[PDB]
Amino acid sequence: NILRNSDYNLNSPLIEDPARLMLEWLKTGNRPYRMTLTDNCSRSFRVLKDYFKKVDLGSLKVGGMAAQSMISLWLYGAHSESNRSRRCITDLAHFYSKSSPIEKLLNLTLGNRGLRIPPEGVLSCLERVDYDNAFGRYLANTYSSYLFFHVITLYMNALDWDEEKTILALWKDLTSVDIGKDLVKFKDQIWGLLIVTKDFVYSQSSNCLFDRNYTLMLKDLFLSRFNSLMVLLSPPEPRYSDDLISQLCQLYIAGDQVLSMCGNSGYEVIKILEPYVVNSLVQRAEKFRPLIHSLGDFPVFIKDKVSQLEETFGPCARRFFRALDQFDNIHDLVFVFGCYRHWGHPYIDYRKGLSKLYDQVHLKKMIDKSYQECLASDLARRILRWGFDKYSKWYLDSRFLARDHPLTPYIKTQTWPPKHIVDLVGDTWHKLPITQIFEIPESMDPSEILDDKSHSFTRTRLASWLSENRGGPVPSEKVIITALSKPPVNPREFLRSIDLGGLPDEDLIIGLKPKERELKIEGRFFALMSWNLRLYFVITEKLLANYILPLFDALTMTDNLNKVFKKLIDRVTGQGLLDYSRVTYAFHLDYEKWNNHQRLESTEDVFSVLDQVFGLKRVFSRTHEFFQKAWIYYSDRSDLIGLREDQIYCLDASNGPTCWNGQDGGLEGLRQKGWSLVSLLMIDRESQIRNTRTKILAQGDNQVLCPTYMLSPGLSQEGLLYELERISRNALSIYRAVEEGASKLGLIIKKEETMCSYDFLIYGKTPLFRGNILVPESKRWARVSCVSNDQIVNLANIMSTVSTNALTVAQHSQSLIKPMRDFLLMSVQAVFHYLLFSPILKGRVYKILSAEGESFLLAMSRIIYLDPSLGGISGMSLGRFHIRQFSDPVSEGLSFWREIWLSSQESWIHALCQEAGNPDLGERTLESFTRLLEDPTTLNIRGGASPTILLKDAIRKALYDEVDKVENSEFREAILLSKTHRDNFILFLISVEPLFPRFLSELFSSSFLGIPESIIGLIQNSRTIRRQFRKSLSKTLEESFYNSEIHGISRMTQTPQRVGGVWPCSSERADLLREISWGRKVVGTTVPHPSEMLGLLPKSSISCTCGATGGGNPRVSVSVLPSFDQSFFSRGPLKGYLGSSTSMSTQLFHAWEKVTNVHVVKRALSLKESINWFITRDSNLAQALIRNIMSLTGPDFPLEEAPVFKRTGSALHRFKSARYSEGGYSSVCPNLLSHISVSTDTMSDLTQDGKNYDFMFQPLMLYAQTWTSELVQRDTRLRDSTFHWHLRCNRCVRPIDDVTLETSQIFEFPDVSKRISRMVSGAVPHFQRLPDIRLRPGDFESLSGREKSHHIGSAQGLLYSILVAIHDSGYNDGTIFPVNIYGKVSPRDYLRGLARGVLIGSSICFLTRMTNININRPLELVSGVISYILLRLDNHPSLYIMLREPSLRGEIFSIPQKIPAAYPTTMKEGNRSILCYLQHVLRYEREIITASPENDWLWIFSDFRSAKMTYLSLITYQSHLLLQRVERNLSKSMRDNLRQLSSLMRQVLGGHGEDTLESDDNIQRLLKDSLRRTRWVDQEVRHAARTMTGDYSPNKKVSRKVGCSEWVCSAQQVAVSTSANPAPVSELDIRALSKRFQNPLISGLRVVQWATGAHYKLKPILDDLNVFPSLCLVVGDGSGGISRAVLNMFPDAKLVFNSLLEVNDLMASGTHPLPPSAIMRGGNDIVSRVIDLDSIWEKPSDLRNLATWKYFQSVQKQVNMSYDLIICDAEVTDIASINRITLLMSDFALSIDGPLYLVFKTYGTMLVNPNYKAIQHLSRAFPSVTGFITQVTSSFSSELYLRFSKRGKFFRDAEYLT
Amino acid sequence: RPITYYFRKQVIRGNVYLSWSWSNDTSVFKRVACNSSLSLSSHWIRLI
Ligand SMILES: [Zn+2]
Ligand SMILES: [Zn+2]
């Protein structure tokens, strides 16, 4: 006799049948059988008769027409005023002003960070103009209507008379009551007189009637409008106009007019609004690069439909589209984009939509099959290539195959074939009988399957319910209840039964339900299936998502937001670049009913291939057979079913069908992944045959193609237009090909609706304008107070949705100040509503509102800012805006509060901080330690933790005392085992001394107890609880929530906790707080926050005063690029750095399902992987883990002989890449991050003594990125000033002091293999145990540098080449080539060792790539394989880092090497040089290696010492000796041994072979060749830097006895250049001079090249110069070159490099760039007589700015010297840049007093164009001039090196050229 | 000047062969109005 409400916001669909039926009942008769009988509706009908004995009944309106009146009414009153809205907004602004000081915290943290504060005031935004005006009357009426409807919905969703009495007690002068009946009236000057009759609403003035869902809709839209305009008001910067607010009021009124004079049918107009905005955005994009041809017919489509809707529907649509086109800005248009729901939702016509669906599904086609054959052949080719790559083993069976087929020899030899062979069989891979690859699990975790999905009925119960009932809608069964009733899943057996036919005719039912808030009158329909069918679909799609989707890259379904952004950036490079080097088109494809039109005959062969690879057949195929053989019905109407005992026989099937017994098609939300696969394969085929460099993005419906094209840097207009013509041609061709393929598969594509652009893109309502992720804010601020389903309206929940909405806004945006201000405002609004009324508390609060002066201040501050862990349970600290997935919120909060404490002088904030310091700890007993298992990094608190723990424990109680009433025996026994052993195992876990809590959590969830806890946390639905359990659980939970909110408000109004002085070094406080909470020392969780250990104020490299004095001060360097544009048109050159992000917090860019766990056995195996990190082998915890995995299996398990390595040199909060690791979320949009690089190599100083600091750099990088971007965009002058952050706390920095865990207590586990089958029996496949050989020791730290760097090199090469030969992801990771090892190593031996390692890696790749004909040519094979490895190594970036150490450079350039010409030395040239040295080592000096018998032993290291790499390494060495020990062709015995090695690596490297097939044959095959020729070490390479590697080997070599190398020059020629004012002009001179030719002969005779071969030209001028200048200023040049020659000629000379950086994305991730290679080629003396070489990038290079020249003057002042020479060699064809250059160079030379010589390179052609402004602009300090020409200059070129000279203080105001 | 590969063909007794020239007009041509690879010409000159 009691039910919950669970309905506040509009999540349900919308419908008109209830109102119609209630009207028919009110007119006359009994209830018409379809009315959802209850008590509420009965009493409502009673009162409704008692007031509808009037006469209005008979001309009443209903839903679908009722709105019509309403909206008109509303716009009328919205432009009328009242006396009520004044009071409301007056009180709201009073609340804000009472809450004004709150913002002080924000302003204080921004002033500590070093930024200005907006002075208008976010929080006093409702007192500038919000009254007595049109806009303030529309705002106040909107808010008042929202309040009205909120009160209405509260009265509706109340339960008892007491709540209604409470409500009327609160609102008195607004509401009225009539007792003796339940007759409640609500009046208002706008909306007249409503009569909310409990579950129904009636309007008299607007003569209509309706139900709750409409009230929720209107409440939601009014709230959207209000909060949107609110956050829109008072922003910091002029991002928007004010005519945005005025235009948006106009737009909303236009929509009102549309609705008021076109009915619900006018809801097609917003469906046109959205693409209209998109078209406007595109047409505003092309203006920047307007020279390319825009394709498609999108704008024509838009114009036609606007004219259509203007002719029909009246001129209202005209007004709407006019006001929509009124906008001009871009962000305003996006803000209009977000509000496609601010008008309402349409009353759907389910019959109409179902009729259209029936027709669209039953529409037969005449499609082809050969296309699908080719498509599936491509798929099988891809899957087999992947299989061979990862696991070097085919997946065929020659026993079933032919012989006149090239693959029987290419299978007898386990290889992969070349291009011409695959072309010979390009479309026949199906005729290959592909066998099983991916073993499926015999069980699965319930967290992946069970969910509140409203499982359907089956035929038996359906027929019985129809025979019993007389009508009404179906309530469907639930999933967890059905699961607890029936036995669990055994997918192997299930799919084998389906393989045998299976899925009998009974369980083939589907039910429909209309989707919610989709804005279509026809309405979408999401389905709910039966148990077996839903099981089939779910396990199938999860199976594909696990082991198929990772192959494809477009497939953006199982991906989070960060990875989405990474993919978009990768597929958008070439948008908004300012040049014509990267043109990327974007085709958005949106088919017509893709789901329905996807049909059987298409998906037969692709699905067949999937089914063969899983070892099944026809199973996937059967899908459409099920849709052919299945019933389909509609839930909200049952009386239409008339079943004939054989089929459906639907009734009333003339007005439109409702049900049917079969359909050739599919439905939305089902098999999205396979259908996406086939569509993607089509697209990829067509593109790859037309253009290979296409990228694809696909979730299944909103597909995106992106073809990229590169065009040369220097191109002329004719050629440019030719290129663009060919570009458009190819793009149109690909689009036509896609349409042809789609008509070949029945998928019709709308030609006039596919979108095309080149500077725009869309993905899932995420717009990307010119590479910039542009944000809609309106969706997210509209979702304020719109809590999710099956949740409670608690303070915590609404504040949490506010916070996460704002944080997702920030992740979609930049300029965090705006989302912070919006967070504040929306939070205050939400809490004002919640305190106006609290449902679960069943009354108003009265403790916070009545407060004044200070107490209300403390209350709000505690509500909003305090974290859930620190006393409060509602708010969040601002420190979560810096990073999102941080490992410890405690340190973040404490750092924030400390900064706010010492950065202030006020009183109450001190009290708040002291409260945050000592958060009122409580008991230290059991029933609290469990919290550490559900959410570590928390505190045992007096006042309870998040209600999740409370739900888990309450449901645990109900399930323990009602275990007997669950039918299943396995689940029953599992819960039985749970009860006892849970307490006992928690006791053991507390019995572990060091208390590393993450290990305990993973162990608790990894044992059998994770099963019940899993499902118990999977219970979150109130109706689920009411069905399964009884009123006890629900009542207990309600009372618990009551007590919890009471304690919450008591905490928010606690006593001020009088101050006790500030605290130092917050993280230390957190550690000791955990300590005094849980007694013992704690580790792991305590992680510092960069807000503490990087300081507040950064400083530019200039004017910092650190330099190199005081010591090796560490720092985090931030190189910003000059391309920084605060606007949204450039996207920068770079990619960005965001980090990784684990998808375990419901952030998948949609919300369909989650990925909580995988399995208990896999978690236990992960523990076994982490055995030796912090636990010893022969101990009690190792015994426990082995007992655990042996309990969850049989005692006959082939354990893996857990390893014999020791990563003692590592951290402890880097446990696993499962839940929290890889810190970093990049809360700010990456768009501005395209301008930034962030280096940490300075922090290498921290490892001067070692100590194993090993702290995470990613939070540092991210904090720096965020706040330096903010500090740049607030001051656009420092567009190139590299910053550097210094450390402030040293006590934050923590030496690891590695620790171990041990106990004396032992705990025995019970058997769970003979007690629970079907859950654990076969979850994980075989492991193929290998026998160990004890890995004879190393004895490593007894050698010198020159004796072991060879070993290090060989090890690195071996590991890299192995990780390349098997396609692991760790082939391109920086953990292999670290940077703390090049500074102290012998370079020659290091590189020769790399060569050795690469060679034996080539041995393994030879073992793999072994066909039947390549055997007789093995030497060329070895060479080519080495070349392949070297190619992949060229693709390795971070190797080029080794060019920082000068010793390595000297050794690598001692051999001839092609010198580059770019300053920012890239991967390409650096790796090319390294690989040229390696290729010179090989093929000249191979004899030196593999000889000198004490260089031959192979020392392996322990960076990847797992069983996998081990046997692979021994195999590589054996195969290397066997390729060696040979000079002539091979023998058959050698081939036999090699095939045995191939089989062995096949067995070890997973697959489906036998495990090893022997041990004695193994040892006999590897002994005497590898085992007694490896010397394994129990140590990692990095820490070797301690003992001997750190001891530098002084190079005691000098030279090679070569002569003095006398220097040389060449001829020259002088020319005159005079000047005067008038400057007349002739025509023939321009005619013969201004014609630029090009003919390279002498540019090729310029043999030497350093940057471009210019020193040849600049020898003679300086040889003529007669000062021997001490100080040159070289500018514009790329590298060395001219500068290097300057250093040659004048020994007593120094230099100022103004070489531009122009960084590219080919560099490393964080590290700083390296100096120009040319100068590092010079030598030590020449380099030291450069000023500063390792600090150039820290200096600016922007010639067009002034700071560069101020830096030059600063150098002149700091050094006791004065400039004498200047050189400018900037080649530019443009004009403005060189004009600026000359302006600033003139002001510079005017700011020099001493003698001066200047050299300017120029082209004679520009010397007569009057727009050059070079001589008349530069000749303002120099009287003396002479032009110079060289005997080496381009054969036809007007190159002049003009030399100016002065002696001091000459002005010569201006003089043109004569 | 722009680059214009003028293509044509010839027939010898029996079969045919192709022919190309820089200075002719037989009206089946491939043309490009930009070199964009003169650096390669200089490279070949340095090599030889
Ligand atoms: Zn600190
Ligand atoms: Zn500094």
Image (cartoon, coloured by chain):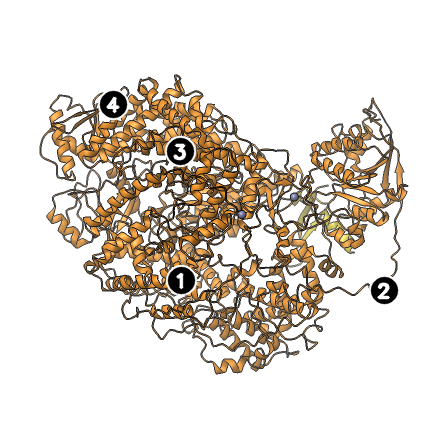
Chain colours: A orange, B yellow
Kind of residue at disc 4: Leu
Element marked by disc 3? helix
Note whether A1818 is above or below A544 in the view shown: above
Q: Position of residue A882 (x, y in %)?
A: 50, 43
Label 4 crowding class (10 Å Cα cut-off): few <14, some 14-19, many 20+? Answer: few
**Can see residue A726?**
no
Would you say the residues marked 3 and 1 are in contact, meaning their CB atoms lie under 8 Å apart? Answer: no
Residue identified by numbered label 2: A1601
User: Is label 2 or label 1 in front?
Assistant: 1
Element marked by disc 1? helix
Say which quarter of the image contains residue A839.
Answer: top left
Q: Position of residue A1148 (x, y in %)?
A: 41, 48
Share a chain, discs 2 and 3? yes
Instruction: From the viewer's side, name the closer residue of A1597 and A1043.
Output: A1043
Note whether A1626 is above or below A947 in the view shown: above
Residue identified by numbered label 3: A826
Report, in whole angstroms, how far the alpha carbon at label 3 lies from the one at label 1: 41 Å
Residue identified by numbered label 4: A174
Element marked by disc 2? loop
The subunit letter for the residue under badge 3 reads A
